[PDB]
DNA sequence: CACAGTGATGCAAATCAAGTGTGAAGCCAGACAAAAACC
DNA sequence: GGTTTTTGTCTGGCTTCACACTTGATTTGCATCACTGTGTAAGACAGGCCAGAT
DNA sequence: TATCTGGCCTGTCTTA
């Protein structure tokens, strides 16, 4: 666990809280630029590579058959196995929520320059209302694959929305969503175990189970220390989901998550209280029917991170985390990598 | 206070004499000043002359919107009390304090409040 | 004992002095004036005063003999306070001193003026919308609202770096309308219409928005805000009534660019170029505004309910901000115009023959085309097909021209031609940067000598106003050797000055009819001059505003009747008010500076308050 | 130990308004006389 | 001293005016709060570097 | 050869 300062290039102003990194074969890429795309990079997607602690963000182009998805802050992102990425929800630069879902896959990789295919996936049934700060994962049960989508926030509904509180948000109803990408349909499941709304939580998916960690419940304004197990059964008939509550969970919202090794991940970052960042780190070890959360050695944080009121970041995919804090005002943010 | 000359003491004693001689009668000022001036115009005056210094010593020691509901109620109960200003007000206030009672007077004031505003 | 002066003496002493003349005056009264000593002395004194040219004391004595209670109604104190720029703290100093020295409460204390303000601010008068506005609240007592409109600020969400206060849009309009009520009544009268007539009035609102720099942050606890501001404002431009098969103009703003009548609607400490924060704050304004298009305001004026329908014209925007909010590319792009689809190379070849095709509704279609890419095109081809609309618009603006910034840009171009004419670039193609610096230095010095202009870093309205004259071309010609080019500069400037009044005056049809008639003809020869005798600069390229000025002025004028009256110059002058008020009319604290400025800037724009200051000119 | 503001708040102090008859202050009348400044 | 002008005193009644008190509601006075701006360009000095002088 | 001053440059320090 080594912390390291990162220099940034001329277009550092793109990086904002709510950005996304995607991993395609050890090459990292960047999505969710601040502002609408400019002529320097019309897709708003960037090859994101740190060479000797220097980050150069370099524009990437789309295939002829691609959509031009708007930059999205706090979307639900997810990796799918033939490798492709799922993006659902998010805020647009105009502060609208997209109900849309986009698929990011590589189209071409000649001369170590990458062309992406961004295709829009239509969705019918019980489509989840437009959201941000929510999780989406794919599971595997009896040789069948299914997408799970939980929690998040949206604006009030048209019936009750007032220009005077036009930007007020509220946690979506905690229904678990099963989303089949092959058929383009979506089924909602209300569970008595999930009564509270929850967003900015951590989602770990192994086999046919998804773990819901931490997060913030807006109605109660509490960051739960609970853990929730959701297992999806995929038989020939109706798929069913069972929710189990497991004591000994983390209390943290907005935390990041990287996979260090098979069956283990690290949790870092995030907030314990509105004005108390979570400086501790957790190790998660996954058994077939067991999950183990254990304290691990804190990193050698600097006096900037310690006293920063906020921080943000994301997993880069190799067990390293790209971390940003608001800096001086010049360069608005200060960026660090954190290896494991 | 004031300090009085010999001629002034003279005029005062003449006014006292005239009052005792003629009680029912009202004196004219201009004529009385004339006749006092002629009577004053060497021994008679010595008494007043010595009285003036005693008065000088005396001068030394002297040197060293329509109305409130209470107002509406007050005005009506005023006639009865008169039959029975400061004492009136005290009685009015004590009885108004001892009294749903003042709801009608305040309804009248409520009607008058819009009339004052416009 | 030398006689003392008469005025020093005691009442007794002056009686003895005037005893001789007292009786002498008494005879004259009984003889000539019925024994009225009071009135014959009052008149003798008054006449003695005016004999000594001392009319003030005579006039004051006259008001004492009558029962003259001199005091100013509070709303009149408000008007004097607001419009003379006195602060409450200074006005309280004035009030206090007047009352102490005169002994009379001529000016009202602040608690009264503070109560007088209530009528003039949003949320006082009642109103109703038929049908009810969508997503807007039927409450009618809503004054200053938090401009973040409930934007999520928990440490998980996006960071909130701005502070903002606003009026609800409808609620603001009502207060504006009620402020204009006397002037709407008078306008009907002067059109020979029933005062009580209540028909469907139509209100045309001019909409302006503006970014400022150099707004220093205060010390003290709060959000670390940026040193920039954005201001959204509206101006009521004209009101007509429908009386038969006619639209009768009952109000038209006389000074359509005056800070007096640009009303503030939203102040925020934010960067206009921070799209996320700009749309978070203003989205509730454009929602309120959209709802008002589909409804009729019924509001009570003079006892009689009146209906009002509203037309919103967003024209107080400079080109940079138009492009940001209508999803267009930035002004360097090859798509040079916000009004047409022409390319900057085509604008230099054709020059004049283009018509207005862009619109808020087209741009929304085009974004969606951009986003969806329905012909599965290459980026080049996709961009060509949507003509540079690669972002989703979020504000409806009129396709127009801002006369202030147009005026400024054109002058800045002429200033560059003057430089290049001095270096004889028409004859010598290449020249070093040092060689170019000196061209500017010559021109800068000469403009100081012959025009009294000092040099400035960035071009000004007044600089533009003073540079674009034929006296200035005379000055510049002294520096250019070739008189074949004195002729070209003189003509180019003559054409320009035949053109300018069209896009600047309030009614070109009434004010420069021959200028309006000849525009298409004159703009052709202007364009031909640039292609012929200025080929060195205008071959393959032209500026945005030259294009707008040359190709769209006549159409805009017939669609709208004016260009100048819809300019941003009024909203810009409001910025000057922003700065003054932030210093000297608000609480010096981070969490009240915006609402105090908003409230007091609204007052400063009240026509009801302004009228008390034209009372001398009855 | 700079300093005169910047506007809104809210609490204390003032003011108001009504009933009517007390005393206190100034005033008038003619005439002459204290003090207090000047040859 | 003689002389000249300020201030009175003597009286009965004339007018105008402040005051007397209580109650609840307005209208004024005032201190309080955390922050504002005016302080805002260039010279002195040391230490490295290398070509042309010693 | 073997040093050696002087400009030159950059950079910090002092007051604005
Ligand atoms: K002006
Ligand atoms: Mg500006
Ligand atoms: Zn055009």
Image: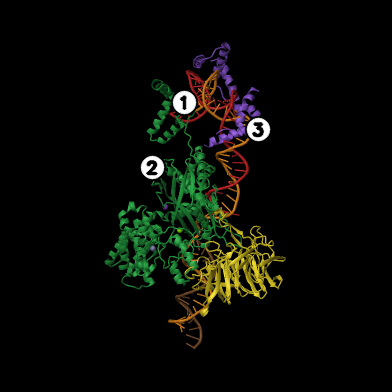
Chain colours: A yellow, B purple, C green, D red, E orange, F brown
Between marks 3 and 1 in the image, the one whose residue lies nearer the viewer:
3
Find residue B5 and report its horizontal and vertical position in percent. Answer: 54, 21
- The span from disc 2 to disc 1 (Cα, nearest Å) is 63 Å
Mark 2 Cα within 10 Å, few/some/many (few <14, many 20+)? few
Q: Are marks 2 and 1 in contact (CB under 8 Å)?
A: no
x and y percentages locating residue C75 in the rendered image: 49, 42
The circle drawn on residue B101 is: 3
Looking at the rendering, which quadrant does residue C532 occupy? bottom left
Q: Which residue is mark 1?
A: C15
Label 3 in the same subunit as label 1: no
**Mark 3 burial class by Cα count in 10 Å: few <14, some 14-19, many 20+:** few
Mark 3 vs 1: CB contact within 8 A: no
Q: Residue at x 56, y 70 (%)?
A: A103
Residue nearer the viewer, A311 or C208: C208
Label 2: chain letter: C
Tell me the tag on residue C190.
Answer: 2
Which mark, residue C538? none
* Circle 1 chain: C
Alpha-carbon distance for marks 2 and 3?
57 Å
Residue A295 occupies quadrant: bottom right
- The quadrant the C terminus of chain A occupies is bottom right
Residue C239 left/right relative to A253: left
Q: Secondary structure at mark 2?
A: helix
Q: Reply above or below: E6 against A120.
A: above
């Amino acid at each position: 666990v080594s912390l390291q300062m990162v220099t940034v290039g001329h277009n550092i102003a793109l990086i904002q809280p709510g950005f996304s990194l995607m991993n395609f074969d050890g090459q990292v890429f960047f999505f969710g630029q601040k502002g609408w795309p400019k002529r320097s990079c019309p897709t708003g997607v960037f090859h994101f590579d740190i060479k000797q602690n220097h980050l150069k963000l370099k524009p990437a182009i789309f295939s002829k058959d691609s959509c031009y998805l708007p930059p999205l802050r706090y979307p639900a992102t997810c990796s799918y196995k033939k490798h492709q990425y799922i993006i659902h929800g998010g805020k647009t630069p105009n502060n609208e929520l997209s109900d849309k879902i986009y698929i990011m896959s590589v189209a071409c990789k000649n001369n170590k320059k990458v062309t992406f295919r961004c295709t829009e996936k239509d969705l019918v049934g019980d489509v989840p209302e437009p959201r941000y700060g929510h999780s989406i994962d794919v599971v595997y049960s009896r040789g069948k694959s299914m997408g799970v989508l939980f929690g998040g926030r949206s604006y009030m509904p048209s019936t009750q929305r007032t220009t005077e509180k036009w930007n007020s948000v509220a946690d979506c109803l905690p229904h678990v969503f099963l989303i089949d990408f092959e058929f383009g349909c979506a089924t909602s499941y209300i569970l008595p175990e999930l009564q509270d709304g929850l967003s900015f939580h951590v989602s770990i998916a192994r086999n046919d189970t998804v773990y819901i960690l931490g997060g913030h419940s807006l109605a109660s304004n509490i960051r739960p220390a609970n853990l929730y197990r959701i297992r999806v059964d995929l038989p020939l008939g109706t798929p069913a989901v069972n929710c189990t509550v497991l004591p000994g969970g983390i209390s943290v919202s907005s935390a990041i998550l990287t996979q260090t090794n098979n069956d283990e991940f690290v949790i870092v970052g995030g907030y314990q209280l509105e004005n108390q960042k979570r400086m501790v780190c957790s190790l998660v070890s996954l058994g077939d029917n067991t999950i183990e959360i254990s304290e691990m050695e804190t990193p050698d944080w600097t006096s900037d991170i310690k006293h920063s009121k906020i921080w943000f970041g994301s997993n880069m995919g190799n067990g390293t985390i790209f971390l940003g804090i608001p800096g001086d005002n010049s360069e608005a943010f200060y960026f660090y990598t954190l290896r494991c | 206070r004031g300090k009085m000359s010999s001629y002034a003491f003279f005029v005062q004693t003449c006014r006292e004499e005239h009052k005792k001689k003629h009680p029912d009668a009202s004196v004219n000022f201009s004529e009385f000043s004339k006749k006092c001036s002629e009577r004053w115009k060497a021994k008679e005056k010595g008494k007043f002359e010595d009285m003036a210094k005693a008065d000088k010593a005396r001068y030394e020691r002297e040197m060293k919107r329509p109305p409130s509901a209470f107002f509406l109620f007050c005005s009506e109960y005023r006639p009865k009390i008169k039959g029975e200003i400061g004492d009136v007000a005290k009685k009015l206030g004590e009885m108004w304090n001892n009294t749903d009672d003042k709801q009608p007077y305040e309804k009248k004031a409520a009607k008058l409040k819009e009339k004052y505003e416009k | 004992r030398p006689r003392q002066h008469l005025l020093s003496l005691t009442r007794r002493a002056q009686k003895h002095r005037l005893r001789e003349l007292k009786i002498q005056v008494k005879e004259f009264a009984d003889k000539e004036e019925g024994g009225d000593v009071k009135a014959v002395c009052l008149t003798l004194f008054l006449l003695a005063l005016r004999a000594r040219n001392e009319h003030r004391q005579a006039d004051e004595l006259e008001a004492i003999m009558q029962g003259r209670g001199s005091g100013l109604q509070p709303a009149v104190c408000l008007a004097i306070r607001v419009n003379t720029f006195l602060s409450c703290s200074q006005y309280h100093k004035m009030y206090r001193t007047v009352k102490a020295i005169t002994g009379r409460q001529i000016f009202q204390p602040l608690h009264a003026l503070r109560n007088a303000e209530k009528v003039l601010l949003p949320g006082y008068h009642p109103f109703e919308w038929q049908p009810p506005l969508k997503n807007v609240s039927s409450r009618t007592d809503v004054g200053i609202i938090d401009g973040l409109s409930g934007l999520a600020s928990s440490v998980d969400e996006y960071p909130v770096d701005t502070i903002a206060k606003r009026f609800r849009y409808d609620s603001a309009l009502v207060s504006a309308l009620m402020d204009m009520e006397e002037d709407i009544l008078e306008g009907m009268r002067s059109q020979d219409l029933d005062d009580y007539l209540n028909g469907p009035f139509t209100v045309v609102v001019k909409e302006s928005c503006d970014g400022m720099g150099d707004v220093s942050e205060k010390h003290g606890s709060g959000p670390a805000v940026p040193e920039k501001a954005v201001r959204f404002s509206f101006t009521v431009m004209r009101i007509t009534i429908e009386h038969g098969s006619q639209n009768v103009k009952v109000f038209e703003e006389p000074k359509p660019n005056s800070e007096l009548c640009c009303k503030p609607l939203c102040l925020m400490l934010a960067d206009e170029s921070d799209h996320e924060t700009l749309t978070a704050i203003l989205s509730p304004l454009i929602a309120e505004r959209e709802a008002m298009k589909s409804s009729e305001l019924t509001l009570e004026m003079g006892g009689i309910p009146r209906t009002f329908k509203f037309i919103f014209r967003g024209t107080g925007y400079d080109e940079k901000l138009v492009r940001e909010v209508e999803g267009l590319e930035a002004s360097g792009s090859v798509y040079i115009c916000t009004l047409c689809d022409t390319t900057r190379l085509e604008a230099s070849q054709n020059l004049v023959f283009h018509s207005i095709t862009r619109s808020h509704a087209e741009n929304l279609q085009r974004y969606e085309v951009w986003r969806s890419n329905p012909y599965h095109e290459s980026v080049e081809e996709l961009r060509d097909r949507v003509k540079g609309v690669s972002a989703k618009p979020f504000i409806e603006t009129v396709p127009s021209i801002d006369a202030l910034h147009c005026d400024i840009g054109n002058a800045a171009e002429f200033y560059k031609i003057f430089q290049l004419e001095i270096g004889e670039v028409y004859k010598h193609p290449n020249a070093s940067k040092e060689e170019r610096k000196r061209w500017q230095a010559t021109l800068d010095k000469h403009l100081r000598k012959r025009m009294n202009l000092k040099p400035i870093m960035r071009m000004n309205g007044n600089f533009a106003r003073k540079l674009m004259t034929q006296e200035t071309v005379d000055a510049v010609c002294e520096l250019i050797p070739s008189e074949e080019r004195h002729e070209a500069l003189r003509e180019l400037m003559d054409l320009y000055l035949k053109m300018k009044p069209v896009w600047r005056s309030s009614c070109p049809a009434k004010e420069c009819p021959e200028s309006l008639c000849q525009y298409s003809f004159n703009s052709q020869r202007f364009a031909e001059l640039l292609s012929t005798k200025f080929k060195y600069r205008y071959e393959g390229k032209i500026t945005n505003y030259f294009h707008k000025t040359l190709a769209h002025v006549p159409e805009i004028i017939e669609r709208d009747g004016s260009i100048g009256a819809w300019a941003s110059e009024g909203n810009e002058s409001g910025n000057k008010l922003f700065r003054r008020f932030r210093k000297m009319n608000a609480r010096q604290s981070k969490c009240y500076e915006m609402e105090d400025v908003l409230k007091h800037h609204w007052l400063y724009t009240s026509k009801y308050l302004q009228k008390f200051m034209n009372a001398h000119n009855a």
